[PDB]
Image: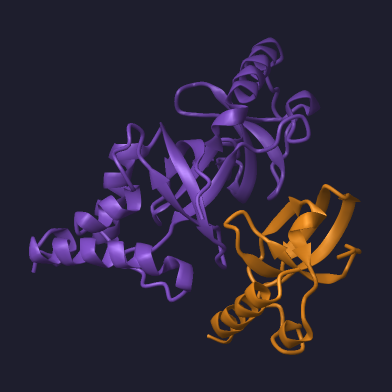
């Protein structure tokens, strides 16, 4: 799928260019508990240790430290492929 | 990726998903239930101080005659209210006379819903109802209402996909279903799953040769 292709490309890029200031509404990459990176949006900033993100392609939500966030490169923005899950 | 968390598996669904509780918070849950059940015994819900609406929390009196935290899903009629037991994962249709108000002392703010839904990584849920029942039955027999180790493998459109390990190093639960011919392998393409997928496909070849279950004919 477009999504699988994008994820492969993005992961490649992150492993070649490993990673940010979280703000409500801002796009990012987020490292999930599987240790892998996904596209996300910052939904709520409760504190540095507690950023509430939404995984824009999968629909899951998670509170995590901002140390597990990074910039989403223009090559993997929502213009390239829209969020695959409904926020 | 390998971070194994001890979980208590509480419910296997007919779609071969399952609900687990984090062993860490088990005692807090235990305390809450005893506190809540004492309250309910002193202050039994009166009809009809509770009006069921989709989305609304409640207490529900389960088939063991005990009360649990729940959330209302479909309301068919006052005799038929669909509820979801938030700490365990099972669902039930009950009359409004077996429901009550969930008082704030025992709310999700005091202690969050304790059950989380997961699916097995690397396998296909059988589409045939009979085959799927056979797979669910194997999982119910082997892990339902027991402690397991859980490792999150990846995100998915629905709940995350995980592997489970039996207690006493008996091995990978999903892989065991493959070895028994009860489920087929989902061939993941991601690089980090190459080795595990090879392991699963080999198990599946073994089930095929032995002509087990799905491979009977």
Q: How is the image coloured?
A: by chain
Q: In the image, what residue occupies the spot 72% across and 89% down?
A: A80
Can residue B32 be seen by looking at this rendering?
yes
Expressed as whole percent of the image width and height from the top left, the position of residue B84 reads: 57, 43
Query: Which quadrant of the rendered structure holds the C terminus of chain A?
Result: bottom right
- Image quadrant in which you'd find residue A24: bottom right
Query: In the visual, does B217 lie left or right of B190?
Result: left
Expressed as whole percent of the image width and height from the top left, the position of residue B24 reads: 60, 29
In the depicted structure, whether residue B158 falls above or below residue B138: below
Of residue B69 and residue A55, the one placed in the foreground of this image is A55
Query: In the visual, does B103 lie left or right of B154?
Result: right
Expressed as whole percent of the image width and height from the top left, the position of residue B13 reads: 42, 49
Of residue B80 and residue B177, the one placed in the foreground of this image is B177
Can residue B124 be seen by looking at this rendering?
no
Q: In the image, what residue occupies the spot 88% across and 62% down?
A: A22
Expressed as whole percent of the image width and height from the top left, the position of residue A69 reads: 77, 62
Q: In the image, what residue occupies the spot 36% across and 65% down?
A: B195
In the depicted structure, whether residue A34 falls above or below residue B147: below
In the depicted structure, whether residue B28 falls above or below residue B77: above
Chain B, which colour?
purple
Of residue B8 and residue B70, the one placed in the foreground of this image is B8
Chain A, which colour?
orange
């Amino acid at each position: 799928t477009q999504f699988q292709k994008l994820m492969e490309n993005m992961r490649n890029d992150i492993a070649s260019h490993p990673p940010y200031a979280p703000r409500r509404g801002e796009f990012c990459i987020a490292k999930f508990v599987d240790g892998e990176w996904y596209r996300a949006r910052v939904e709520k900033v409760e504190s540095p240790a507690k950023i509430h993100v939404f995984y824009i392609d999968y629909g899951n939500r998670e509170v995590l430290p901002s140390t597990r966030l990074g910039t989403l490169s223009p090559a993997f923005s929502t213009r390239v492929l829209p969020a695959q899950a409904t926020e």
